[PDB]
Length: 128
Length: 130
Image 1 (cartoon, rainbow over the protein chains, first blue to last red):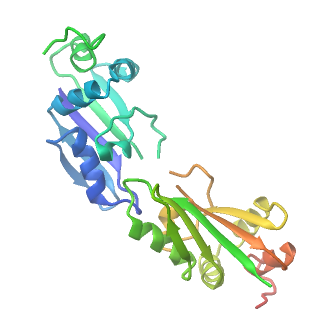
Image 2: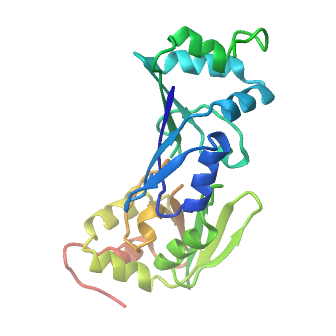
C-alpha cells in the first residue's frame, strides 16, 4: 500500500498548519510544495489513520466511503482538512473548502483485504 | 451623510489571521476588524479610495458596475470579493461558496444608489465625480 496525498495551500493559508493537519493523520509523510501552493505527499503507515477511525467510532462511514472511492487497484477518499488540524477525520466531497485528497495504491493485497484492515465490519474481529 | 461599509468572512483553522486581515485591508486600508472565538470576521470601513483606485488600475468597471447592480437590495448593496486574490489586492467578484470570500455590504444612508454606482463603477470611460 502506497499513500499518495494531494491538496493545496491557498494564499491565505499557513504552510505549517496544513502540513500538520496532514501529519496528524499520516505522521511519516514527506511533503513537497510547489511555488503555487500545490501539495504533493507520500506516506506509508496506516497505524494512526486506523487508530483514529476506531477512537472516533466511524468505521461505518469509513467502510462505505472506501467502497465508493474504489476504482481498480486504487482507492481515493477525501478528508476535511480543517477538522484534521485537531486530528479529527471527516469524509467530505472533492469540492470542499480545499480538502486532503488521499489516494491509496494497493500493490499486492486484494481490495477486500484492505477494506477489513482499515474499516472492518463492526468494531470486531479484525485482521492485522 | 455616509456610506457604511460592512465586512464579513471567516478564518478557518488552516488559515492565517494575519494574511486574512491584510487581504481585507488591501481593499479597505482603514478597516476596523474583530474576530469572534470561532473565526467569524466582522469589519467596518469608510474610505472607498482604495476600492475605486483598484477597480480602475485593473480596468474592471464593467464587471464592477454590473455586479453592484446585481447585488442591490434597495439601500444595501452586497458583493463578494475573492479573499485569496485580495492578498495581492487584486479585485475579483465571486459567489458565496468560494473555497470563504469577503462579503462586503455597503449601507447607503443618505446617498442615492444610482449616484453610488457612477461613483464606484461609472459607464464606459465616462464622467468621474469626487
